[PDB]
Every structure is written in structure tokens, then in C-alpha cells.
Amino acid sequence: MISGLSHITLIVKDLNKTTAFLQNIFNAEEIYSSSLSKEKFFLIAGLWICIMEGDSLQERTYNHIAFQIQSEEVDEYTERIKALGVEMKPERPRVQGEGRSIYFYDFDNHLFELHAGTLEERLKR
Amino acid sequence: MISGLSHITLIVKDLNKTTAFLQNIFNAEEIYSSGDKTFSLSKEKFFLIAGLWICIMEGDSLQERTYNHIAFQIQSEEVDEYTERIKALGVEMKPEEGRSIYFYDFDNHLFELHAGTLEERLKRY
Image 1: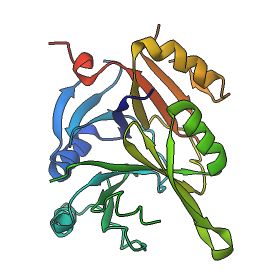
Image 2: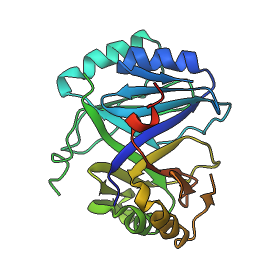
Image 3: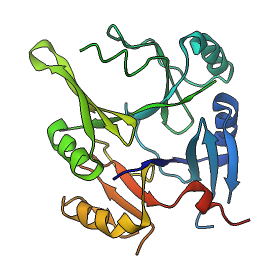
Image 4: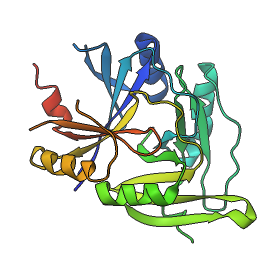
């Protein structure tokens, strides 16, 4: 059986610029630096994230990872995002029981979500 | 502060096919299903995999394959097993015994099953 999540790997054109983005917004903790290729490992809220430098670029889509935050934190995270001038999506339509979320991109078409809801709340079906 | 992973969202062209894929390889557990075509409401399902909340929505598949990917953890003893398990589903596998397995679903998503922990990966001290 699957024990759980091992890690998430992302490809970016500029590793040092992405590093700063991760360290600033997600308080990412760099735990490794290159090797087969140029890469860095970060710990983000317990999750092992791998960033590799490459010219590969996925077209933008709703395929994304979302991190858990608290409702009372949506505004502060919003100010933080605006400050770095990163691109933010507008309010997405949602149903009752679906908490607030903010969406923004990195520099390589990676959509990230900060969700203030709980799976339990969305199970009023 | 970001407390952790909320969920992972994947867009697929055919949920039924993808569902079976998730069930056969990851023992994915379906816990939610919505959608109503006569009401112009696209379908989506929520799955639990080794405790992780995974969301699937119907839409276009990635139009190209990249190295960005999600890696799930397993045991070294289970590598040969999953290798065969995945081969039996007929999906493409990257030959890249063994410590890590790479393969695509039906929508150009690259998955990895990885044996070994973060600690193990960074033992070089």
C-alpha cells in the first residue's frame, strides 16, 4: 500500500529566483542543494518539495497543489502575495461548505492554492 | 502559518477511466462525487490516498509531458510488485531491484512511487 506522499517535484527556469519566491511566501526551509542536474530541496509545512532547473514549461491549467491555512490568515497571505507582485487569480465561485481560497502563480506556470476550508465541512452531501 | 497540504487537484479527460486507475494502483478511496451534465455542472470526485485528499475534475489532459511530478512513497520490498502492478494497467513506464518508479496516467501526468525516505536521500553528511 501507499504509505503517503514522498515529495513533489517542480521544474523552473531560474532556480535562484524560485528559491526566493518559496522562502518568502511559504517560509520554505531549504534543506539541500546540488549532481545529475541543478536542484534544491525545501521543507514546506512538513512536505518535501524538490525544485529542479530546466527549460521545460507546462501550459497553464487547474492541475495544482493546495496548502492548508486558517480563515483568519487569508488577508495576511493576500498582502504578502501582492507585495511580491506575483500574479493572483480573482475570487473563484464556490458552494456552501467550501471555504475561502487564494490562488497565485510562481514564475513557471505553477498554480498554487491556499485553502482555508476543511474536507469535513465539504462532506455535507 | 501554513499548517500543511490541503489537497492535490488533477484534471482528467475521463473520470471513470482515471478512477479505476487510482483504485488499481493507489487503493484510492472515493469519498465524494458531484456533477450534473443536464445542469452544466462538470463532474469531480474526491479520493483519499494514504491520508491525502486528491481531487479529480473533468477537462482537458495536459497537452505535453514535463518532468513536474508527484511522488508517492512505498517500500523497497514493494518495488517489483508495483512495477508489475503498473505494467498490468498498460500505462507508459519510464525505465528510469529499483528505488523509484515513473509512469504516466492517461492525461500526461507523471507519477512516481518512491522507496526510501527524505532522511535516507540526504544521508550524505
